Amino acid sequence: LTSVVFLNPGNSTETFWVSYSQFMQAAARDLGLDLRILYAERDPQNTLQQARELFQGRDKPDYLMLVNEQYVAPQILRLSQGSGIKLFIVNSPLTLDQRWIGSMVGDDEEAGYRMLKELLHKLGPVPAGHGIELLAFSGLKVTPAAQLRERGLRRALAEHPQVHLRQLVYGEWNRERAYRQAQQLLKRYPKTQLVWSANDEMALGAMQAARELGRKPGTDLLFSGVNSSPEALQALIDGKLSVLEAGHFTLGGWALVALHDDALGLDARRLGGPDWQLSLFQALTPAQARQLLRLGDQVGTRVDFRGLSAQGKPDSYRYPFGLQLLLR
Image (cartoon, rainbow, N blue to C red; front, top):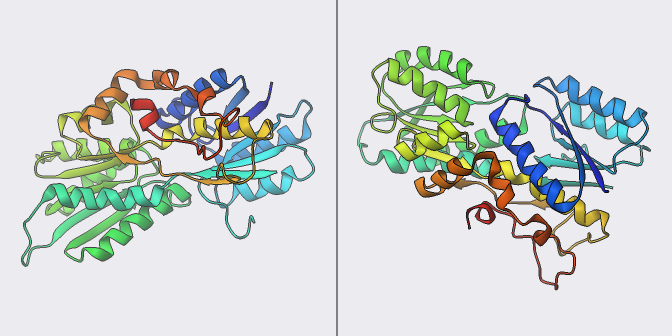
């Protein structure tokens, strides 16, 4: 069977990355692919070592999938030379420096931009001499997911001078860290009305700090987040979390459909390869959140991956990759 090894950067207990893995496994089973997922447990050096040893060992996989980063990815690209293994870079774009090797990315910048626009929309009027104070919690500073989401935030801020970013801190995707930072920041900047977070874990942490200070998430203080953890989905449904961008946890599954087809020789143009650019993020509605909450990591089982394959498909067929395939 076509074999793929994916180097997962998260912890084996990290909600988002586990959901990403579970969706891929559902795709692997349906597509008849031999998939192995190696967790870095949040230390990029482990990803590098896992790749280094894979290239030096026997029984190499047909494909090696990895998340792009500015320090480890380049080294893995150089080490892969002459390995015979096909590489697939996901989640963020290949750089000019880095430029068979394909890639697949989502729309992180749009998510960062839309979160602020959505928060501003829900907050509603109040202007005329009054500023709208904002706190921002980003992820790991050196990661493209954080950089791209922040770029989107910066674009929205440039369009809304009334919004005053009092401070942007790096919560490193960590809930307790954001919680600790929020305890201090929300006390220092009591006029804060908006809290933009690059992920849901951090939003939930900041929300707890907010409740402890007497603030009311969803009413007098609005929060945004990215991902679809059970707690975040429930908070969105309850109205405590105001905006939740979700959908990118499905990227790995779509990637396997693409690799499955590449192995069959169904590649080239038309289908969108070898560097796919997808729009996966959606600001979830309570109804959609309810569906995702009920299904959890079993959501992939309702997706007909083999049906997404271009195999035996008429032309003009473009992959319909999206969250809608899960909510039908």
